[PDB]
Length: 226
Length: 227
Ligand SMILES: Nc1ccn([C@H]2C[C@H](O)[C@@H](CNC(=O)CC[C@H](NC(=O)C[C@@H]3CCC[C@H]3C(=O)c3ccc(CC(=O)O)cc3)C(=O)O)O2)c(=O)n1
Image (cartoon, rainbow over all chains, first blue to last red; front, side, top):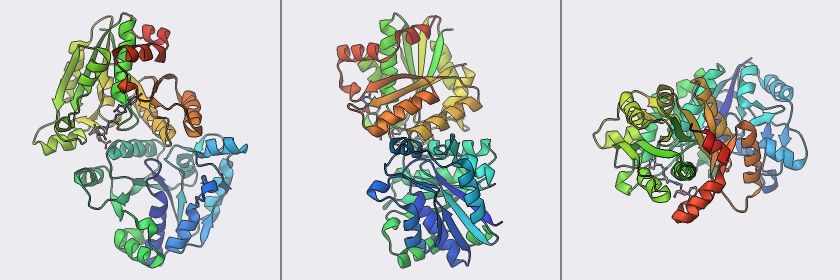
């Protein structure tokens, strides 16, 4: 196999998709083959489609999903409202394992935070990460409350022996502010801050996004991933 | 002693202060003596003062603070900004131990969520709860993300064998949309939902707040909290 990272977050709306896209873009520019798996996508009635954003921003073509629910809710609720079950644990684990190959970086994008139910019955991205022996990249904010949410998420990871690959600040404000700047330092005391993506990077075109992403991560860290 | 409950939350801004006041008011109307303490209060330069709001909303007079810092930030950062130190672990424990008394419900209001550092080094309200043998009441929202944050918080309580006294939904909208209604039902499968306080409760006057508080909790649960 190659390298599988689950990409999780401390909460909903932290910008996991732009982080997946930026790491994919950075890894591709280092000559690494990248695949991204989003097993479950909700919010499709209003056009939510995180895999398409990854394709547009980073140029990834190996983009795998299993299930799409119209309502903008947690997967289990969205599945309930549609009258259909979530995918089964075996579907997710084997899809990811079949994506994995030597020399490839495979990113698994969850929905919301680490412990939200993604598959039947009550299986989370954490469970998935155990099954495929993935490490976790944790997307965080720079806002008030991020320290508690980050610590909580890293404790949950450690409790099932899922390694933390580091943190990414999904949206770095401009200008920062006292809280954001304090939080960036405090976050780096609990884990490695791999990148802080500028606020608004999601709206960039592919060329600008590729330039941002190349600058955003440490080149040796990206290259060492695989 | 009596019964000590730490009142924590899944994040900042979930309404811990109103839940403290509501539970205090309900316990007082059942004849239970109540004290509330706030070991760390930040944002005092903004006028933040949770103890004084609990006193205003519930009439509680047995109010105990310890550390106060001006900037509206996490305690560690607020203390550093002021050139001050965080309290030591044993200082928070002494603040609480001095209030504990048979027949009294002592509420310990955290700052932000459960793993916020309240004392050097990296001492949290979870450690305090172990020290004083307290159970934890967890204030949650009904919003997107609450299920993950609630499960993360309960898992962290279990890791130190801190019992969970239940959840309180800090603000319950009227009417509830689909997300809020789904979350309430899912929260109730994670842990006992003790109350769900109507949104805007902090703007009720003394009498309305008292009535809301009495209606919001199961009288048997409240009465059962303290012998
Ligand atoms: N039923 C109901 C229910 C609710 N209400 C009303 C009551 C109220 O008016 C409001 C609910 N209350 C609010 O919103 C507080 C406003 C908010 N206050 C904070 O955030 C916490 C402090 C403020 C500055 C520092 C922060 C900190 O303590 C902190 C601690 C740890 C960390 C570490 C980490 O990073 O984790 C970071 C920060 C803000 O200032 O933004 O609704 C109602 O009426 N009826």
